Amino acid sequence: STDNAETGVIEAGNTDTDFSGELAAPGSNHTNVKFLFDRSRLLNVIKVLEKDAVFPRPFPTQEGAQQDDGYFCLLTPRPTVASRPATRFGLYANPSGSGVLANTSLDFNFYSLACFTYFRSDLEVTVVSLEPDLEFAVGWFPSGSEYQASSFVYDQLHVPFHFTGRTPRAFASKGGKVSFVLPWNSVSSVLPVRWGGASKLSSATRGLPAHADWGTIYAFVPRPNEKKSTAVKHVAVYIRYKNARAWCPSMLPFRSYK
Amino acid sequence: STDNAETGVIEAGNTDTDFSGELAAPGSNHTNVKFLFDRSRLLNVIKVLEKDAVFPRPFPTQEGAQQDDGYFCLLTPRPTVASRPATRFGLYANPSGSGVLANTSLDFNFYSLACFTYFRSDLEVTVVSLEPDLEFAVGWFPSGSEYQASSFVYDQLHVPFHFTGRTPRAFASKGGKVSFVLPWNSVSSVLPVRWGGASKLSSATRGLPAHADWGTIYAFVPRPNEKKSTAVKHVAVYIRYKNARAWCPSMLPFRSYK
Amino acid sequence: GPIPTAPRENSLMFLSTLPDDTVPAYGNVRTPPVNYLPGEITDLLQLARIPTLMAFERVTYVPYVAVPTQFDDRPLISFPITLSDPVYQNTLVGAISSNFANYRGCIQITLTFCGPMMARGKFLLSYSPPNGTQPQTLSEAMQCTYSIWDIGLNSSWTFVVPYISPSDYRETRAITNSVYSADGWFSLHKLTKITLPPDCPQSPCILFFASAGEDYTLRLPVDCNPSYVF
Amino acid sequence: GPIPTAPRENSLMFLSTLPDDTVPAYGNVRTPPVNYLPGEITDLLQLARIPTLMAFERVTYVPYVAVPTQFDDRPLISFPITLSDPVYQNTLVGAISSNFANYRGCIQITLTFCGPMMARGKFLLSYSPPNGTQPQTLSEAMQCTYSIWDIGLNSSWTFVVPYISPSDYRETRAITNSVYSADGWFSLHKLTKITLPPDCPQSPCILFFASAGEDYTLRLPVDCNPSYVF
Amino acid sequence: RGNNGNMTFNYYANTYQNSVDFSTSGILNPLGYLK
Amino acid sequence: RGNNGNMTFNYYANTYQNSVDFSTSGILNPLGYLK
Amino acid sequence: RGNNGNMTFNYYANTYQNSVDFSTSGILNPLGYLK
């Protein structure tokens, strides 16, 4: 049928427009945005704390600084590095040489279906053990805060402060699982899938949002400082968006042609 | 009573037709097709994955190809071989000599009562361990897809991709069981008990349907690639048709006379 | 506040035959319509009530029986009434019944004469309840339940085995010949010899069919035997 | 008194796709209003129904095709109809479809002529259902479904590929060329050569767009492929 | 109906418990007829 | 609505199960218009 | 009736909880009579 594509708006047609025929029945509605995104998926894998921690310093950190790495996980589909927001995803193709290796993460499915510009939704978290018959706990604090770092002495046994606080802490039995849901607590109204502004008024890095996440999570062993074991331990984190919404179209990744 | 059997249609009678007597009471209705088939039964036994897998290649495979065998199970009453649909059931009566041995399966009860031509029903799955105090998980993907084969590096620990995905994955506690139900998802309207068509337009094998199944199932150990053990493990698969229906009569197997 | 409850001794058990459902995983699926397929089967009795061909030994098996020309007083053919007997093995009634444990109702038998249109004769069909020894002569056969069938225009003739049992329901297999499994014998007698005109083939053949009755019924499913695959 | 109950075999299991919620931890939160953002997306079909540019090989890829001047009977260009084919790879229809398993409805194709206003010509568009071998000449093309499009004032022309399938729903990827994945070919034929006045550039170019139809539909989500990150 | 014992309560919705066919816009009857 | 199967019972209150926006004092419609 | 304490709720249907006899178509009374 004759038409002009330069106008931008083109009306969708059917088989009957130019030939003899008829339209098909609806079928099913599995493409609904709310129904599509309510499925759990892996996000990151982190270690388990066995003592009081030292939060990593900002990125301009030079050598020789003492801190703990790979113990904290951010809750956000965007790329991150060293437990802090980033802009470019990383990958170590040559595990050799000096220097500490930076943790990295990303939400492959979310960015494979990230066809829009802005997003908002609640979020449900779950954790799972990767070691046989392990006892652990999980802690959390909201966006725009920091982790207290010190300990107290009870009966000559040091006890880290992160045991107590008015922000959720949860315990699981031998081989159990931890589950709960969180609200949308960032100051911004919506989470930007892609951004092009600056946060600070000067010396800022363009395109790096400040508070595009839900919070922060970590795991620890409920024992005093006197029982620091000899082997490292790991856990896995699962997230699941709930009651999602989208606001403005965009484009999808570039599938390279061999 | 006088009658003509050549007409094909013969009316069933009772004792009173030719003698003095009476008809018996109904009794019970255990022959109902829906009520008959709602019972679980064994289908196949498979191994448990401990690393990233390589799906077996098509049947014309020559020697020297590297892949993993006996790790995947199809969901279908029809015969299968090497985790792919087949037409003739197999049996190794002389376990000796070179060559890899092909896995096989069949639904003995279903084909012992397969008196019809077409079938359709939902399906409920269950899995059970054959080793003392084992931890495992089960994964699934629908008919007409394929299994992703690669891994990712977290904290220098390789993690297979089959951990994550928007198609169901389930975990069980120590010694637990896994249970859930699936819908009828094949493109075909009904499942053919016996078939005589061809799928491809040329060079096809007659009588081999393309998508007569519900999906595919496998099991894996939730640990990184660095913990590949030394002993093999097995699990058992149970299926149970639900809300079944039949559509056209047929004949039953041939019980050989000694 | 939490509702207090105490689980019973039967917990975490997996029971195959449990009459209940489970949790869904991938719901909200919609499937194509199936209005176009005719002939939906609702109960397997619909198939159990269709006649089929039996088998005998020609000494190596055929469905028919050849009428000889010699004269003797023994029954032409006689087989017991037990669904596990070989003769019913391949017929639908027997094949389906082997998957259950009990049955009721009246069995049905049918015959058809496939000889030349010019022939004439008569046959006697009898059914003998259980006894110490099975019948062996026409005089004995006449006393039991029996009927007379004569060759004419119409070719077939149906016979019904009454359900005469000491108890409701009966076993569908005979591990031992208790009165609840075996139920007598059926035998066929040639009342008069066949008459044929000159230049016609001799020894006509007769054919058998077996099917379920009107008031037939099954009960109590059981697991099946997989030996056929070998 | 305590309510007695018995948990089922499926307890303590973690199922990702389970259709239910969980326990809250930090409730009673109130969030800013979002009335000010326009253009809320409710279904991804709204985006699937927007045309986009396809790709071809210039031997190293361009969206358009250059009309030659030589004369030959082969089709100017022909590509299969299979959403997994490279040509649809980067278009929105293909990109979104690769995340599901089935589809319905009618696909849509659009063209636009970007040559000098002074040119004149005609083109033939055809769609061939599956066969042993694909079409290779105008005589064969005329018989299938086809239409004639002539250069005039208006620049674009839309074409609809009917949904002609042996079964409801079809696979969105072709592991093997079963009739349920591949659905024929599409080809373009130059009916007449282009006419241009003196002192004008030769070899005009034509452009392609691909989009979903009115009655297009998807179903049965599936996990995505992360290879793009490399 | 079927091998289902519950007759009082259903938790999940029908469209999630079962599959359905999308729309388009007693004694046993015999099989095989003669006329 | 959504990937939620329950349709009969809710235990916790709405303001604790979900987040809400504080007040201040069918077929798919198209995107992009021409006039 | 019997050694059964529940008097309010039954989950499964009667025909699945108990066996039944298919149809066909106070003070204690004494045993043994004289006339």
Image (cartoon, coloured by chain):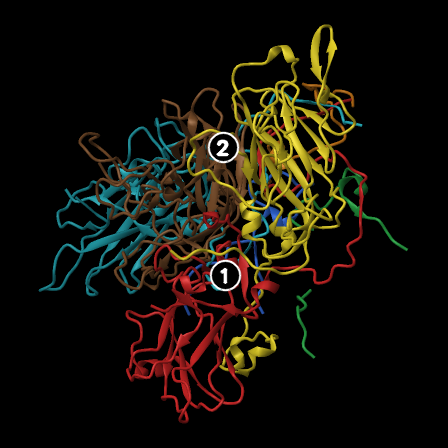
Chain colours: A yellow, B brown, C cyan, D red, E blue, F green, G orange
Q: Which residue is mark 2?
A: B137
Q: Which mark is residue A48?
A: none
Q: Which residue is mark 1?
A: D103
Q: Amino acid at mark 1?
A: Tyr
- Chain letter of disc 2? B
Judge the density around disc 2: few (<14), some (14-19), many (≥20) Cα neighbours within 10 Å: many
Outermost residue toward the bottom in this view: D197
Asked whether B82 or F21 is in front, the reply is F21
Q: Amino acid at mark 2?
A: Ala
Res. A108 in view: yes
**Residue shown at 33%/44% (left/top)?**
B79
Outermost residue toward the top in this view: A155
Query: The residue tagged with tag 2: helix, strand or loop?
Result: strand
* Residue C212 at x, y percent in the picture: 41, 48
Query: The residue tagged with tag 1: helix, strand or loop?
Result: strand
- Chain letter of disc 1? D
Report if the CB atoms under discs 2 and 1 are less than 8 Å apart. no
**Residue shown at 74%/9% (left/top)?**
A154
| Residue B195 vertical position relative to residue A234 in the rendered view, above or below | below
Q: Quadrant of residue B99?
A: top left
Asked whether B94 or D15 is in front, the reply is D15
Asked whether B91 or C135 is in front, the reply is B91
